[PDB]
Length: 277
Ligand SMILES: [Zn+2]
Image (cartoon, rainbow, N blue to C red; front, side, top):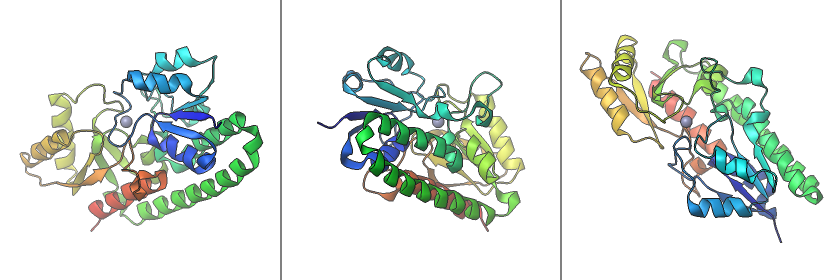
């Protein structure tokens, strides 16, 4: 029979789909709209995890509530935190007390994670190494093209206009790779809401910098960024909500936004369209 691969975030499931295709059974625990920072594994999830031959998760403490679940499963199956293969020097350190887990927004950096998915699959099914390698090389070429595309789109926007404010601070790697100044209403983790103070400071930032738009996300209730937009207006500045971005989760299955390449493409197109003119 075919082995079972269980993944957390959809971005990782996307890599498994492209590299392993039908050679493995794939179960993604977190679908569209799911916040990985706040996610608690259900009993059904733990069942799937307990039957998996390979478990792939992000690491870098993204899945803040699943550490123990993963801990207890090592020793009986391959468990790989794909993003922990990214060199420490390339990770963004938060006040020397945590690493930013949103590595998928620097496409070149994400190639390390994709390589880990590919290599883990080869360990799982060594007999499939050749086809996995062909599919992986094709997928990596798509990612190379995606990186170049995002960079062109970013460069098409005036430097002064490259200021991105979103529902939470998920674009730190995007900021470094593509030349954007970024701020989020909630922090790198969504574990805590933004305080009244945090909101006034960001509202002041938005008003003083005279930004054209701010963005909502598919995994955080729109209510908060909408309340933020209101605070900005009470400060004499009119900012609009430029669109909804995919931060921690991808779009629906069947749509291009339900793929890693489509998710990123949607984000850059949406951002550039709202920030331009
Ligand atoms: Zn996040």
